[PDB]
Amino acid sequence: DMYIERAGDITWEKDAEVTGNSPRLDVALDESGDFSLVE
Amino acid sequence: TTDGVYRVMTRLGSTQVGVGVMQEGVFHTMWHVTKGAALRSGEGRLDPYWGDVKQDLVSYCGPWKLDAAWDGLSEVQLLAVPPGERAKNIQTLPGIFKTKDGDIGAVALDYPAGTSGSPILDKSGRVIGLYGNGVVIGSYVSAITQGKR
Image 1 (tube, one colour):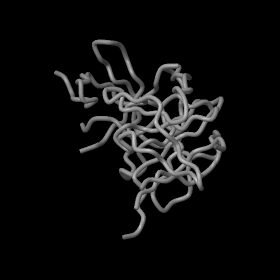
Image 2 (cartoon, one colour):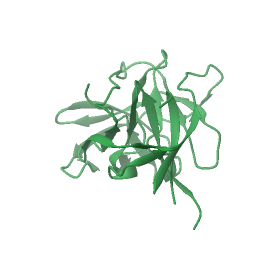
Image 3 (cartoon, one colour):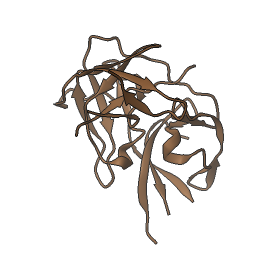
Image 4 (cartoon, each protein chain N blue to C red):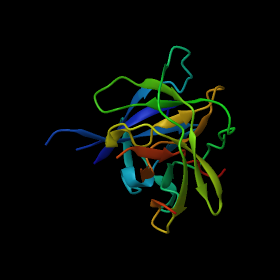
């Protein structure tokens, strides 16, 4: 059986660590909800 | 019932299978997390209301309520709730999924599978989508998956 526990407010944090790139990708979305790359 | 971000847990012992957003009396998560199974909240039960495998989304108690969208220029924050860890905000500039049906924001952040369903936020604090359906390029990239209101 599945259950939920509260973990916090939905809020923006000004002191947030900043990371990660911003790649631009060609993709396709199939009927099962799976993304795949396209070339 | 209370607004906020929530762990989705399952039961020998408990495991965190995902994350979701409670807003306006509706619980929002990704289909692959719950497969639409009913959810326990305290002594109450949350019953599914809408779901779609292609969008990989599901809502409980009512229709999908989140409708803010990435503005295409600004940094966002993943409100990651990893298993065993305090909710934490990770700021990033999204990349882009270019598809035949239009462009989708995407975040190049890689957190444990039980983080699936964590909300992505804009600067105003609005949920612009959920984390955890994506592609690999060894690096995982998640779509910013938003439903329709």
